[PDB]
Each structure stands twice: as structure tokens, then as C-alpha cells.
Amino acid sequence: VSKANVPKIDVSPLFGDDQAAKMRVAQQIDAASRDTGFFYAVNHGINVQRLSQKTKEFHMSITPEEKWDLAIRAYNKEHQDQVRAGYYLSIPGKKAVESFCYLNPNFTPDHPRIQAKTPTHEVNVWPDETKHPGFQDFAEQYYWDVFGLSSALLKGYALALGKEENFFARHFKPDDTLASVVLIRYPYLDPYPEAAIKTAADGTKLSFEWHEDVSLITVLYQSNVQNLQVETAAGYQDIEADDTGYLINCGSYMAHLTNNYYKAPIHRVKWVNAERQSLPFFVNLGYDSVIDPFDPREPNGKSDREPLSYGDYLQNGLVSLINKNGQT
Ligand SMILES: [Fe+2]
Image (cartoon, rainbow, N blue to C red; front, side, top):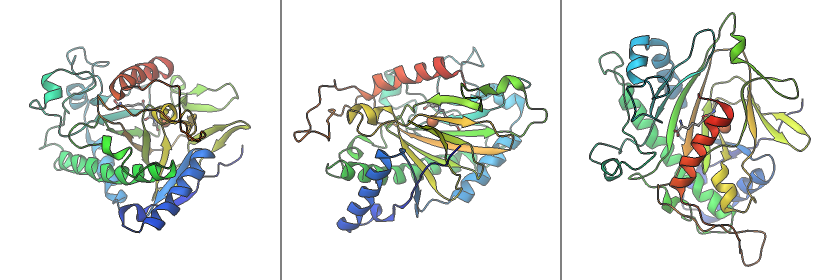
């Protein structure tokens, strides 16, 4: 098994005003997006050691009582309003992974999309402040930190495609973004439950099967344990881990609006029996956001693809991924 070429891109110019320097970052984003589809963003300015420490404290101290109280509908029939946001329980002896998902902190009972009961909008659920002091403050702060990084990355993607730098970012707004953070624990277990390991066609033992992401882009921080593979024409290649950088890739909405010029890379998660964290931020736009598809290969950029509202895309895509790869 060979190793993927995943470049490290200093994204710090994307926060500045040196336009030539932004263009040089954009070129590197374009090159990586047309190759394996992944790159590491470095010099990003986020305190990832505090991110990992506070996430670890939460996963290790939450009790079965609290997990039931936070559980999404798939694990708790009482919580009909929690499809996305809440706790995704492990099943001892059967399912190893457990996770906690939260959405835009601005989604409150007073928010108009919540009042309208619009699909894919939910109010976050949180543990008791006295049992997890400072956790909600940290998690909401983190949402806006990675929102900021993601805004800057979207400027790079726009310039890479020959668009003005706000082409995507204008649709990525704090008041309505459907972006989510998932705090995922992959545990060390001895014996490891065989029901939690899948075998791929090529014999590789997996924790999560091949998929494309449901996102515009995905902005991922992982601890320093190698696990991801990306599909190429010549087979799957290992993505090296780096627990100081953010791993970036496009989701299938980008592939749609660029007529597959920037593909959504197919990737999968190898089984590794090690305690590790996986903290993705899925960059989603607003429910009514529509970007006219274009084709950068054509002089006039003309595309025959239909515009797709981000809300409809997200609703269909989340259901599809559960049905293909299972309830997480
Ligand atoms: Fe993924």
C-alpha cells in the first residue's frame, strides 16, 4: 500500500491583505484539489492542543445516564426533535465509535428557522454545566474559531477557481450556516468487537467504509494515529497523520457546482486498535443557499447542471450516508 501525496499548505496569507500571496496559496489548493483531493492546512492559528484536551475530558467523564439524556432519536425514541444534534452512543460488544454532534449556536428557540420547524435545523443539547464545567463555552468558542478558519479557506477555493474571493464565503454566514462539529471517540478495546470491524473488497479491515462527504468542504482535526485512505485509480493510498494541522477535502456539493472539476474524494477509515479522536467540521451553507454550477474547463464556464438548494442537498445526503454506511 502506497502513501498519498498530501501537501502542507501555509494558509496564513488567506487572513491577510497581500493579494499575490493569496493567489500563491490558491494555486496550491487547486493543485491538491486536482490531485488526491486532500491537503493539510498549517499555520492556521487554532489552539488544537486545548481542543483535544477538552474533548478527551468530555468523552472520558460522561456517564450512561447523561448519554441517554443527550441521545439522538436513533437511540432514544423520546427525542424526536434530535436527528442531527446530540450524543451517538456506542453499543458495547457491537459498535465501538461514539460521538457528540452540535450545530450553529445561534439556533435558539427564538431563531426563525427553528420557529418555522425547517428541516435540518435543531437546537443544540448540552450536558449539565456542573458535571462538565466549561465544556459548552469551549465548544461554542471552537465552533466560531473553525468557522473563521473555514471562511478563509473558502476564499482560497474561490480564487483557485478564478472567482472573486467571496464567491463561496458570501453564503457562509453565522446567522444561518448548517455547519456542524462532531466530536468522535474511537476507543482502544481489548478484545475489539468483531461486529465493529468491516472487511473491504480488497481485504483491508475498516472502521468506516468508502464514502464521499456531505459538505462543501470538510475541515478535520485528528489525533496522531494513521487511519485514513483515499481512493485513486491505482487503488487506496494511506494519508499520513499530522496532529498539528487540519486535513481539508471537498464534499459532494463542491463536485456538483464545479461539474466534477474538484471531485469529492472517496475515502475510508482503516481499523486501528488505538484510542484516538476525530473532530470534523462540515462546512455547510444556509438552507436556501444556491450556487449556480459552472464548468472551469470551458472558456464561458457554461454548465448544464441544475442549481441545487443547499438545504435539499443536505437533507438527501445525510439520509443517503446513513443508509449506505450505517447509523453512526
Ligand atoms: Fe469523510
